[PDB]
Length: 66
Ligand SMILES: [Zn+2]
Ligand SMILES: [Zn+2]
Image 1 (cartoon, rainbow, N blue to C red):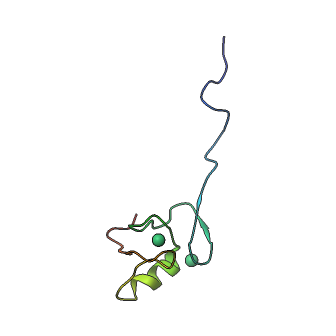
Image 2 (cartoon, helix red, strand yellow):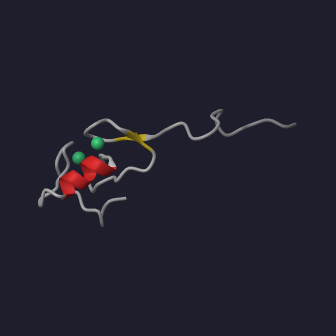
């Protein structure tokens, strides 16, 4: 009377990737649109005055980023 029940996947099987260099990361900076970027590319866009999102282009703000 002992056996798994919730799915059959062990350990976290998923990650993120930058929407620029496709750099696979664990904790990206999800903007206010959804897409994600890497520390680099991220710091680059934000330093563009009007950072949107290379992906679709919406808005990239460290404060609004996670
Ligand atoms: Zn990148
Ligand atoms: Zn986007």
